[PDB]
Length: 105
Length: 157
Length: 104
Image (tube, rainbow over all chains, first blue to last red; front, top):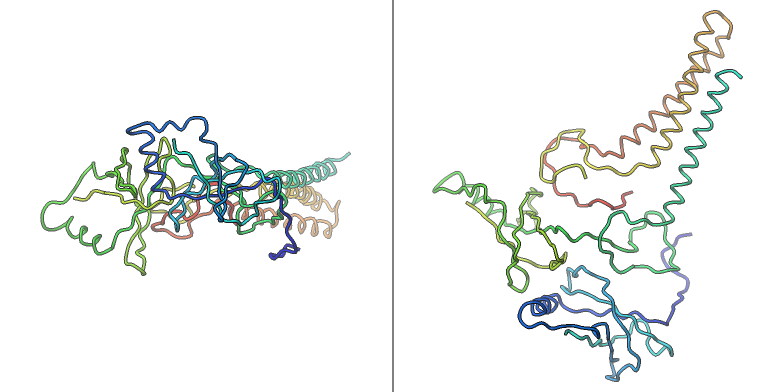
């Protein structure tokens, strides 16, 4: 009772979290240019996020994002954000390396 | 009925009341109340995971952003140098404006709001010969994040 | 967290509060048992002078009273643990743990 190692794992493949990362200096210069100077005006489609797989092909569906990690990592020096993607045919697997494509105004 | 039997009766009643209070707070632990207010992070575990009492790994993390501590290190040789310069040589005493001067972020940009210093660690580390000093900073619109490399400027005599 | 970091502290000064909520309840239970057995032993002490009650009954009534008196002290020290006191005097470092955190 209460052992550390598991016996099996159960996973829900639909939907899929996509945790992507970006360095804090890029967020700093984006926040500086977002207010000072020209206004980037992120608008309505700032929620829109589309990704590509490691082979270069585009994922057909499209998902939104939400912020979930306000603290910057000590070792990497980068902030991680999260996105939700619908996965109706199990084409995405947990642990896959992907490239998200954002919209910074 | 004599007074001693009534004393035993309400003594047993109060003991059962304490027992049902124990069971009530054990029921209250099943709904994990947030101990403080602040911004919450990503949940480390999700629905379906088994958790035990007093486990080491957390399930989520809440934190408060305003105000924000900064911890900057100083070599002890410079500390004893300025300490021997305060009481010898030429004049060195900053005065009432020796609270704090500003911070510099990782991109080299200046920070608008100056903070305040309060000392919190006098135990010099044996690995690098440095002490850790501590300062507070206001963070109104959350442009600072906890855990980033910064360069704090500060005052001496 | 009832101290300023980097300040001097005297021995026995309260530093934190660990939200008792259990030790308070068993302190109430021990207080109820002591409040019963104390007046029990006092009434038997009043009766034993006129030989209305035997000496054996006064003996084990006083024994149960002292037993409950020990149990309420066993609860009171656990109440004293929920306000952690500085065991010595001197300087204190910064708090490695902060409010809202669970300790075991």
